[PDB]
Image: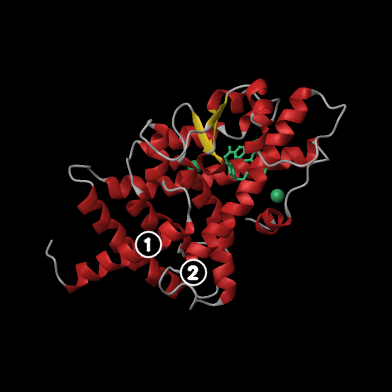
Amino acid sequence: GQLNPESADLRALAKHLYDSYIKSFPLTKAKARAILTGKTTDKSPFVIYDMNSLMMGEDKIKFKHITPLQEQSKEVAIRIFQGCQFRSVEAVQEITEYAKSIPGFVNLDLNDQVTLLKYGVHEIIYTMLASLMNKDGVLISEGQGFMTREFLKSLRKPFGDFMEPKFEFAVKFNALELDDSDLAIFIAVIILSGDRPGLLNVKPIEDIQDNLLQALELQLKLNHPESSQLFAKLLQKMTDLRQIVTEHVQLLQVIKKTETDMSLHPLLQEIYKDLY
Ligand SMILES: CN(CCOc1ccc(C[C@H](Nc2ccccc2C(=O)c2ccccc2)C(=O)O)cc1)c1ccccn1
Ligand code: NA
Ligand code: NA
Ligand code: NA
């Protein structure tokens, strides 16, 4: 390893992605970790750990008009469902904005840009969800609230099955101890996946991702001394991300069967429309 024009170009690419990452995502992992570990921040999230604390902290969740005469277990799960829906729609906007700053991305054919984002957003959502998670729960509303793992698991069937796979993923993923500069390149690697179904021009996508993989490999070398095979371990996580997406779609399908009075936002519809 030597510091030559090629390595300096990979370091500049990493910095450009970090900067775009910082301006596209308001709550970074560094900020979330400070909150979660009790460092001094401008945030003190209200903790939601049961139904009583959920109602007393209704402001943190964005939900529609409460349907009266509903069993309270059902009304609570609908509030959480609509709250995650709002955040997901918001998260997709942040991701598509960040993708534009990936060098070469907007120059790809627009059909392939849509395809890459269609298949990548949820993998990235779950990657960055881990940044806001510890073994106790997840930060919500940009750090204004904290919803516990066990409360999310206690929701009425089948709502209590949605978050658990993300927490299982997150505790293992967070043991890699990646930071925002690592994550900015990693999510770009996810977006530039040449194996998405229906891509027109695969070679330019693979060429960009090859450049991103070089940058990510160098980033982990410089940022994680004595961390053995972190590059390979991180790339293997992408397989876990895809299983989570698949498992999640099948959970959404049982609600489309089980419950009316709970349609999905048209954007999430547009994304899941013919997903695999
Ligand atoms: C847990 N959480 C943080 C955000 O977590 C996300 C968890 C998942 C997602 C992906 C997103 N998921 C949903 C989309 C629509 C409706 C429900 C969900 C749920 O996933 C869900 C379903 C049932 C019960 C609980 C959740 C997607 O498919 O697009 C995006 C964000 C909350 C919770 C309440 C309010 C806001 N923040
Ligand atoms: Na799998
Ligand atoms: Na898989
Ligand atoms: Na669907």
Give the x, y percent position of residue 60: 62, 37
Residue 205, percent from left and from top: 44, 70
Colour treatment of the image: secondary structure
The outermost residue toward the left is: 2
Across and down, in percent, residue 123 comes to 51, 50
- Look at the numbered disc 1 and give the secondary structure of its residue: helix
Query: Looking at the image, is 88 positioned above or below residue 164?
Result: below
Is residue 143 something one can see in this rendering?
Answer: yes
Structural distance between the alpha carbons of marks 1 and 2? 13 Å
User: Looking at the image, is 274 positioned above or below residue 106?
Assistant: above
Residue at x 45% of width, y 37% of height = 170
The earlier-in-sequence mark between 1 and 2 is 1
Q: Residues within 10 Å of mark 1 (few under 14, many from 20)?
A: some
- Residue under the image location 57 percent in, 52 percent down: 91
Q: Secondary structure at mark 2?
A: helix
Disc 1 + disc 2, Cβ < 8 Å: no
Q: Nearer the viewer, residue 189 or 242?
A: 189
Q: Amino acid at mark 1?
A: Asp
Is the N terminus in the top left, top right, bottom left or bottom right quadrant?
A: bottom left
In the picture of the structure, the residue carrying the numbered disc 1 is 19
Q: Which residue is mark 2?
A: 100
Above-or-below relation of 13 to 108 = above
